[PDB]
Amino acid sequence: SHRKYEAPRHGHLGFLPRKRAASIRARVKAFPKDDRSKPVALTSFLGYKAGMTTIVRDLDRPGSKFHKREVVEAVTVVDTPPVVVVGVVGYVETPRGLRSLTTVWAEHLSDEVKRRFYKNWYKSKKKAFTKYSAKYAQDGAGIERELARIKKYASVVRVLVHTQIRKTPLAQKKAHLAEIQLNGGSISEKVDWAREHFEKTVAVDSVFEQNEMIDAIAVTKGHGFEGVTHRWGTKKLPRKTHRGLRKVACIGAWHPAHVMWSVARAGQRGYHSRTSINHKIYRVGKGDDEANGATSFDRTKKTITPMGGFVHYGEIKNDFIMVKGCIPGNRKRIVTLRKSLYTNTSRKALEEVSLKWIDTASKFGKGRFQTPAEKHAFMGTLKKDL
Amino acid sequence: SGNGAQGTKFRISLGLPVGAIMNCADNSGARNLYIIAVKGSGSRLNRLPAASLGDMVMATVKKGKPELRKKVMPAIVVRQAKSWRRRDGVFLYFEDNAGVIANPKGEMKGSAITGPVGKECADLWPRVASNSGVVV
Amino acid sequence: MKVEIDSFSGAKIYPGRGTLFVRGDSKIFRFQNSKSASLFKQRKNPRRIAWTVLFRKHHKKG
Amino acid sequence: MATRTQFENSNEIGVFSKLTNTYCLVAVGGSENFYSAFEAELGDAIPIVHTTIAGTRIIGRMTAGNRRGLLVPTQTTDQELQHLRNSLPDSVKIQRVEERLSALGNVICCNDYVALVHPDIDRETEELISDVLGVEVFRQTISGNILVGSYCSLSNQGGLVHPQTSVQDQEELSSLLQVPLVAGTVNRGSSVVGAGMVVNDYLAVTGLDTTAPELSVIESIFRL
RNA sequence: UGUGGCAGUCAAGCGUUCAUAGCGACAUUGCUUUUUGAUUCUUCGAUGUCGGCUCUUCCUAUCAUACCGAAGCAGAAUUCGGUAAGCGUUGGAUUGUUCACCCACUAAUAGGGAACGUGAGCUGGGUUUAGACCGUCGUGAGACAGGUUAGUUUUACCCUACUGAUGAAUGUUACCGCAAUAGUAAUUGAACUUAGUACGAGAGGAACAGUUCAUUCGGAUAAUUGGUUUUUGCGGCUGUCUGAUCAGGCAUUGCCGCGAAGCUACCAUCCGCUGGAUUAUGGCUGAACGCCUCUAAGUCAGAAUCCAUGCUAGAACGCGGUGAUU
């Protein structure tokens, strides 16, 4: 017999196996294509997702029905502290793919990456990098030898960065060490850029800019063990089914005498790595800039942090990328934001957006006010001080 | 969308599957309409073709004149009562479903439309924009 | 960008928030939340609900 | 002249444009040949304004006005109202209209002298129409068709009405409006005549389906 | 394999002229196991038996989509053929139906397989025991190749398989990686513009590029909107019981109104990429055949095809760099 009503599948067999990720920091599989003429800059940046908010702006799209017209949209504020470089690592190319031949660390690493190298920081004698930071006691001849071995060799040069986690309202105190590749030309210039940026910080006024399309890489919000009707999207069976109605009913045919890899079963849902592409930066805001949530149309001084903070996160007092639409991974997750792999030209990209209004009401309920001064003005005085 | 419909209608919430009995809001004589299909719908296994505001349904008349009953005609849904999202921000919904008897080219069978008329169905269909009373 | 006013509770309505109920005699009702909307659907008189603005204008609070 | 024009292919221009004596309002999504039919026989005589009304492109049926005034519905935004107040000259008076009873272009059937309205519109809006447009407002329906806007094209010279209209109603409205009236069709027999075409003193633009015997009666009753 | 079903071979003629634009008799050669016969080899110390729902994967004898080539093809639409199965083939009335036939929709509503897929998946409407009724047959018990009505549908805790999850040992321990191999996904329409232009006696009437939306699918999130509500959070209400106010108990979450957080929905929102090599075919020089010919040597372009770019896991005995090494 055939299917008797030929219909599409459920799910996608290219996102298999749907298991848990390795770590919570999703790897970047591919950095953008190298261009050996550009000035040296990073290809990705490690931020922390805070949450969403609403944006009123002017859609200016010729030939569209909403031309010159105000639309509301959802964006995610991803918190972004500045990020400090602690080492470089260069890869030579083999007939078995790339291979890291040497890595060079900084002089005096902070207590956020020294805390990354111990599972139990409290018992430990904190003796990481003693005999390595004693290699700067000389003139650096071993370390200049290491950089010469990177200069002579090593087709691509990646830079070990790490976040500044104690500038973040998380309670982790441990920074996520990572590798980010460099696109600037003439790899001597790459490794001299990295040598000049040892222990120096990197802000997102340099990596990302306004209106740019960025990809976003993170680990999905996990949901535990999950049955098949919500994991894949299978129909519920009717009310009359003995032994339940929330299943795939026919697993397989008689022959093949096995369960195929393509049928839908139960297991993990969520906590997978994902990459969502084509997300447009609506804002790049700074930490020392008072009134981050101010707009050229709104002109009222207020930060982007809502009334009573972002829910389960806290208060943005840092840099922030503010990117259109949803992003994989929930709040408080290490989101790696990446430059776009390809030159995009679509007139959905290349659109220059200045915002008009940022929503900063409380997300802890059906919020009503924008700033507490506005609440004190509309509600009036209360049983407190006056 | 479709033939005779002018413009690219933005997607609103599908609120009227096949079987819904909406009010007929023009003075042709039908008291209520009955969806039997939706022009422009899709094909997917065990899924009712749902209409929306601005869509073009095929409709029969259950209450009304004898000349309109027992025959299949087109119609145009002009109120929804399922909350949809205009792009400027608001979610909105009318009180009760409505639609007007038409021909396949979009021309009206009646002369005047009672009740408010959603503006997604006034901009897409021009002839509804002529006979409409309260737009929005 | 216009900040509308609630038809039931007098609160201010920022864009992309609440609902909008066009009634059968074409009067437009703008609701801040589902609280005032689901009190309007119960035909509650706005002057008798003690947290609104039309209450505190009828009983002279302030 | 009587120029036949389509709006992207649509044979009804009165929905999509508002032609008066001192201005002409068009929708934003027009072709080259659509704007050409106005900018040819107008040229640099009256300002032709690309606008939307309340986010719509049905601005001939949303708004209603004449040489002296222009009326917009309640849902018209502030950018659209500012664009209309700027691009039009200072002779015409623009005022928003507060009524829950329709959109204005199907109610108000007006010219520089005498206006007809839908009879359900109220007195507080009737006074505002007679104030802003400066036009004596009466309350009559063409042969029971309550929407007198879309079923009666009107100018200062004459007027075209609903094609199934009694001769007694034609003579009554000719005694009222003080212009001659002839019932006819437009757009290959489409009976919605006030939305099928626009007209003023020196121009009348109709759809591409308006045949030559219909166009002859149009230019005969409008004396062009 | 007769028998269905399908494909060639020749060719009389039909088709305005005219066997071939397309038909294709008379013969004749085959294929298929999606029909039904024949056989009776396996199973009767029982491989649970029709239909539907559900869910995969495969084939192609292609309905649509892509790219081509022909007409009794000007355009438009239609008909046929080729490489093609990457992708999609619906909602219903009646009937237990398979099959059908209508009513719509649609880009189109193609044909099939996997023990006539799928009963320790379900339903049990059908056939098929026992009750019962009717018709005809029978002297009668009873029969039917008939109609109708009521009729217990059992078990997985094993092993494999699949879907997730750990895990010893390769000096210990931690961080950063590489990458074999395996999977891979996007699909189709509409509108504007092109343009009432090309083509046309008229009637009518396109396409390439650009733009905006949508259909189906997929992956994510939850600011907003909607749902949920044991935050029993606040309020209200009835019956009874703590002597009454207050504060409460009980009504197997007592009921009702609102309800954050969490979870969630094409009932919400965002996102879903680009190069190389080819098939059919169209060619370039160019012989074979001192002309000719895309083909033989060589070479240019080319499809929803294939392959990488991208995306998902990562070899738990595939590998590298680096910190510390009592």
Image (cartoon, rainbow, N blue to C red):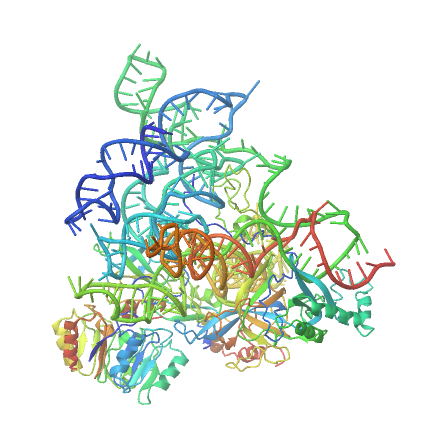
The N terminus of chain B sits in image quarter: bottom left
x, y percentage for residue B16?
37, 57
Q: Is residue A263 left or right of residue C45?
A: right
The part of the image, by quadrant, that contains residue B132 is: bottom left
Residue B134 shows in this picture: no
Q: Is residue D171 left or right of residue D72?
A: left
Q: Nearer the viewer, residue B43 or B49?
A: B43
The part of the image, by quadrant, that contains residue A274 is: bottom right
Establish if E285 lies above or below A253: below
Residue B56 shows in this picture: yes
Establish if A99 lies above or below D159: above
Q: Nearer the viewer, residue D31 or A340?
A: A340
x, y percentage for residue E97?
36, 38
Q: Is residue D9 left or right of residue A162?
A: left
Q: Nearer the viewer, residue E45 or B20?
A: E45
x, y percentage for residue D97?
34, 79
Establish if D60 lies above or below C38: below
Q: How many marks are shown on the rendered structure?
A: 0
Q: Nearer the viewer, residue E31 or E110?
A: E31
The C terminus of chain B sits in image quarter: bottom left
x, y percentage for residue D82?
39, 83
Q: Is residue E33 left or right of residue B129?
A: right
The part of the image, by quadrant, that contains residue E326 is: bottom right
